Amino acid sequence: LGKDYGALKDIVINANPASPPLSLLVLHRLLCEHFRVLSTVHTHSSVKSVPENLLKCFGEQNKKQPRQDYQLGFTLIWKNVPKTQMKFSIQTMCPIEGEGNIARFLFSLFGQKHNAVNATLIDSWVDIAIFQLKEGSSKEKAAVFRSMNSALGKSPWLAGNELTVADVVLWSVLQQIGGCSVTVPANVQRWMRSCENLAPFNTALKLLKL
Amino acid sequence: TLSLTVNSGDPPLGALLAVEHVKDDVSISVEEGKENILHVSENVIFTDVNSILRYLARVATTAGLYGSNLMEHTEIDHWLEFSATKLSSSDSFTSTINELNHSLSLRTYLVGNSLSLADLSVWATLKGNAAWQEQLKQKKAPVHVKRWFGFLEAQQAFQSVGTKWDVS
Image (cartoon, rainbow over all chains, first blue to last red; front, side, top):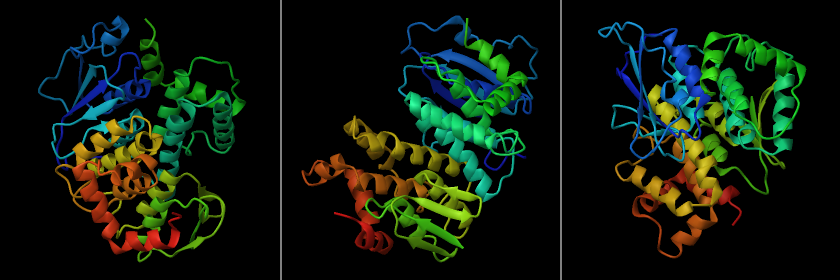
């Protein structure tokens, strides 16, 4: 923890309202638990309308503001983009595309230190959520559940004894998978309930429906 | 030590470039095989190419392949996904290659002014993309991408991996 190497402040996220990034919302609630965050929602002029729940996903904004105080600025822009995108004040950093990459960045702000093996495992799970689970066949999804269930019989969270960005992204992607029935194995069921018991997880999930 | 098995019939040039740019820092052998497996230890293997690249970049703290800070790290993550998704589809390739060209217009390497996993990943994926080859031979490749791709290809590490492993 520290956060002032090259001090950046305002994080901008462009997201398509037809595809709300649930992992980023969960992450946003989590950051708020550790940092003083100033949160704003805009609608880019390339988007005609936006559902009310999405317009006010940062609604618990009625609170008195430190104003002077803010550590991080988090601006969500509903925009007609093909892929969720994060931008910074800095010209040197390219726009970051993909919620998995944005999630990795945001979770890293918590300072969690990992060794080579475990950091790479965490990254692996995020890739699986994005490249296999997000848009895979019924068979590809069944194979993900099997891997998760095996891992979750060995540790309480996907990468070990602590919540990591792996749990955030995979749980989120699972909630937005909607079309065809598949059945969840028992270690995955236990882990889902472990996730849902956390305030940031369930409040962000409620936001997604009216 | 570290052992990488590769699919000899379809080698992961990116991972092999990483092994090449890393060999002076960590002991690692390459085995012929029919799939990509990085054996780290008894209970630890990585089988997907981006995970293999990440792990190698992380244990080789001399090579600097995962950048020098959180922002460069995040840019490298961006490029790893770019090559695995957009650049692997050969679908809306023209738009994807034009995005890559735009990004390289003011850069020499993709991230932080030195060689990183971003370069290895995107280069390897580009070499294996038929639409890229069909652009080069037909003199339609975008200027900056051609410039950066030729630069890497003329490096001795790239020429060495190409000669040994590249199945024309």
